[PDB]
Length: 110
Length: 350
Length: 99
Image (tube, rainbow over all chains, first blue to last red; front, side, top):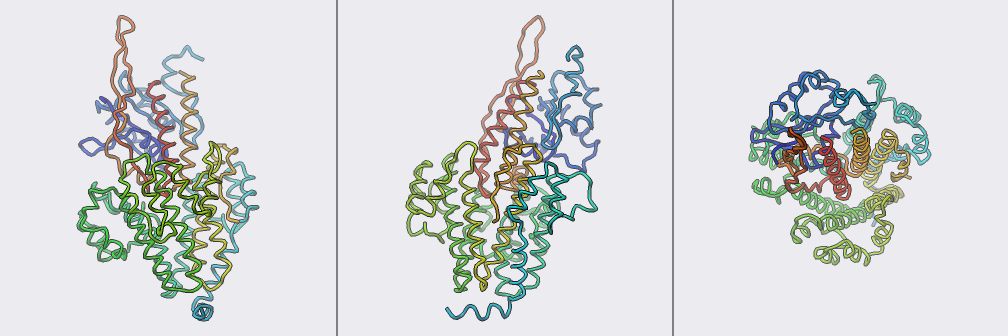
C-alpha cells in the first residue's frame, strides 16, 4: 500500500513486470519506471534513479545488472535503509553472480 | 462457371508468376533443421545467408540480437509487399486493400489511447506496425482531441465504412479498446467475405472456407478466455462473425457456454474442430489448441496453391511467410536462452 | 541470500521463457501493455520487526487488488498471458522477500 515498486530495465523486463502486478502513474502523470534502449545514456538513468530516491513512495527499486553497472557510483555513494535496490539479469545478458554491493558490504562471505 | 479461367491471366499473369516464384522460394523443413544446427546467433546468420535470406545484417552491428533479425524479416516483408502492390490493378488492389485493413485496425487501435492519455502523434508514428501508411493529413497533428482523430478517421482513413458502427466517441472512452478492435475486426471480416462472394469464381472457392474457419476459431477462443474475465454473455456473442458454419447453429451454445468442456461439446458436433480439440490435449509440455489452429490455417494455405486463377495466392503467401518469420523468431528464442529442449515448438510451412 | 539469488535467477529465466512463448503466440502485445498503465494491482506495506534493542525495517507483499488487464487483441493467447502473470507474481513475491 504505502510504497510503489519501481523498475528500470530493457523492454522485456518492463513489459513482463507490468503484467506481473506492479507499475503506476502518480497524480502528476509520471512513470514509476523506465524502459532502457541501446540509445539510452547514463545521465538520464542517473536522474530518474535520484528522482525515485527522493520520491517517498518508491520503497523498492529493481534495476537490471548492466544498468546498475552504468550508474554503479550512484549505488555505492548512496547508503540508506529505505531504497532496497536489487540486481536482476535480462534474457540475453548472462546470469548476475557477482559485483553486488549488498554482498560487498558483507566482505566476510565467500 | 465460365467467368473465371479466361480474364484472370489477361491482367494478372505476371503477378501470378511472381507470387508462385516467391512461394517456391520458401524454406523447407530441411532448412529449419539446418538453422537448428547452429547453437549460436552468428551461425543463424550464416544459415540465413545460405538461402535468399541473410545478407541483410551486413553493414550493421557485429553483435546479434532477436530484435535485429525480427526487424529485418519485417522490413523484407514490407518491401516485397509494397513492391507487388504498386504493380497491381483494381480487382487485385481492393484485395490487397483488405489485406492492409487487417493491420490498419491494429494501427488505429494503437493511435487512440495516445490521445485520451495525452501523447504525441510523432512518437507513435514509428511504433505503428509497417504497411500502416497513414500518409493522409489531419490524422497527424490532431491537437490531441478525440473529436479530431474521429473526424480524421471518418474522412481521410478508408476505414470510415467500418467506423459507421463505432461512432460518436462514446465507445472510444467508455468501452474497452480491446472490444472496439474486436467489433471492428468482425465487421471487417463480414465486409471481406461479402466482397469475396461478389467475385464468385476460384477466388470465392479459395477464400470462403479459410475465412469460415478463421471466424469459427475466433468465436471458440473468445468463449475459452471469457470465462475468467468480466464479460456479459451477449457482449461475447456480439463479437462472433456471422460468416461461419457456427452462425446457423452452434454460436448459441457458445453464447451460453460456461466451462471448457461445454465448448468442447459445441466443437464436437463439427468433426473438423473435433479433431483439432482432441489433438489439443492441453497437456503440460505439449502443443496447445492455437498451435492446432495455426497448423490448420497453414495447410489450408498450402491447399490454396493448387489453383492458378484465384487472388487467394497472395493472401496465402502473406500468411505463410509471416508464419515462417514467427518460426524463425521462435528458433532464435530457443537458441538465445539455451532451451534447446524446446526447439520442436514451431509449426512447419511444409 | 546467495541461494535466494539463485532462486531469483531461476524464476526470472522461467518467466523470460514464458515471455518468449507468449511473444511467439502474440507478437506485439508489449506496446499495448506499456501504453495503458492506470492503477497498480500490487503494493507494498511498510513493516517493522523489533528483534533486538533496535528496530529493523521489513516489508510485506500487500495485494492491493486492482483488476488485471484483459489483453484480447494480439491473437488472444490468454493462456500465455495468465501463465506469464502468475510467474511474474511469484517472481515479485520472492523479490520482495529478498528485499
